[PDB]
Image (cartoon, coloured by chain):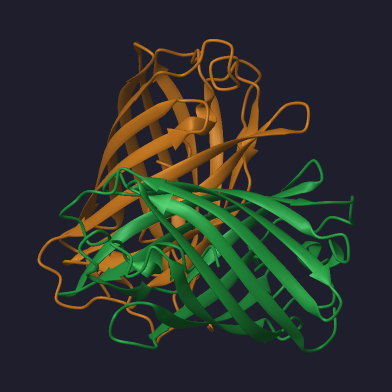
Chain colours: A orange, B green
Amino acid sequence: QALADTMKMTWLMEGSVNGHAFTIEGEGTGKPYEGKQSGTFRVTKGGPLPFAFDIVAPTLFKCFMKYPADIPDYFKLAFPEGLTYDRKIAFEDGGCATATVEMSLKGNTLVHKTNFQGGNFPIDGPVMQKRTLGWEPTSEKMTPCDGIIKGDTIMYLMVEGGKTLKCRYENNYRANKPVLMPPSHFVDLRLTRTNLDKEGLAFKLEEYAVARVLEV
Amino acid sequence: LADTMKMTWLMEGSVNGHAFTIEGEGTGKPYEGKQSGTFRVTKGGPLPFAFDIVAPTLFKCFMKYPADIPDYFKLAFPEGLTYDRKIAFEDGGCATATVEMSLKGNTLVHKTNFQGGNFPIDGPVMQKRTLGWEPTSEKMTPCDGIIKGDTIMYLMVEGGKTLKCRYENNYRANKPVLMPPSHFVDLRLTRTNLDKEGLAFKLEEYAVARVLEV
């Protein structure tokens, strides 16, 4: 196994949203084969953020998924060499972002590095007014194509006052020269945000993700 | 709805300025989530575009639901349900459709107006190089008495290629009904050609609901 039953992780995310630069650093622990992970994050530059931390939380780790033995796990098979992915994030109100993530392995630690560029968020929208309340669970479609996995998801961001904001993710997960691909499948996931202060400089995230094929 | 129902379809529209009409008749088992129909292009045929782009718009009351999840689409009957749909292909082809589903005796009546445009002249849709839709799962999200349907579906293309499509659906029951929680509906839609000219087709679908266990 390139990945052990328990792994440590680190995150470094740099970017800008509506021209506001920021840096987030994190450390965590996860169980790759159980599909569980958690981490503690700090906004080390540009905090308190003028935008909802929720917009970067799903971009803060695809090798943490529970797969049945009869479905190849592209994200773990990518290790030890690692995986890089690009991501398009599009909200229904015109807010958008593009991110590039590199996942690498250093001993017992999985290293996650991201550059996140966001723009066109409405000034009075829930993201810039920080009126969000975490993401509703959803299912990511995983479609193999030309040695990459295309991830496609519709995810709703919860908003204060019983409202929601729809978001579409288009992900392209690229391992180096893969020779085994899974069939098309889905990965169900729940991402929970825990605030660690009142100011918005520290957060904890937890995720559970599990793969399945449709029975149709 | 009875265990077995008859259905009729009337779809009128235009794609890249080309007008067409499709009529169909079929039978299904609403509670088993199974349906099939035979379709004929009665005006504007042979179509200059792939029949596959209208096939997912040709019937939400045919879904297998477990007893502990309310079935919005069946609870909408006998009053019926109307929905709007946005269809967006990754190459810029797009369509908007409005579907009215009604009940008249033992027959479910499906009426659609489908407007499509901006399909690339050399793309798989206008070159009729498609091979049916890959199965997928539709997200169903209740919102103020309606169900928002959201799906990413891949259309198979000759030569081992695909064309991604996004559907954004708004299902509106004609009378308020008990609402389900957010869930997904897995489905497989199969097309079978009934002729060589492209005037007749058979479609079949199996759809089954699931709540996530996360």
Residue at the (28%, 86%) spot, across then down: B196
Quadrant position of the N terminus of chain A in the picture: bottom left
Q: In this view, does A129 lie above or below B102?
A: above
Residue B146: % across, % down = 76, 47
Q: In this view, does A15 lie above or below B186?
A: above
Q: Quadrant of residue A151?
A: bottom left
Residue at the (68%, 85%) spot, across then down: B28
Horizontal side of B8 relative to B115 (left or right) equals right
Residue A189: % across, % down = 54, 58
Q: Is residue B30 visible?
A: yes
Q: Is residue B35 above or below residue B53?
A: below
Horizontal side of B107 relative to A138 (left or right) equals right
Q: Can residue A6 be seen in this view?
A: no
Residue B141: % across, % down = 68, 51
The extreme front residue here reads B43
Horizontal side of B140 relative to B135 (left or right) equals right
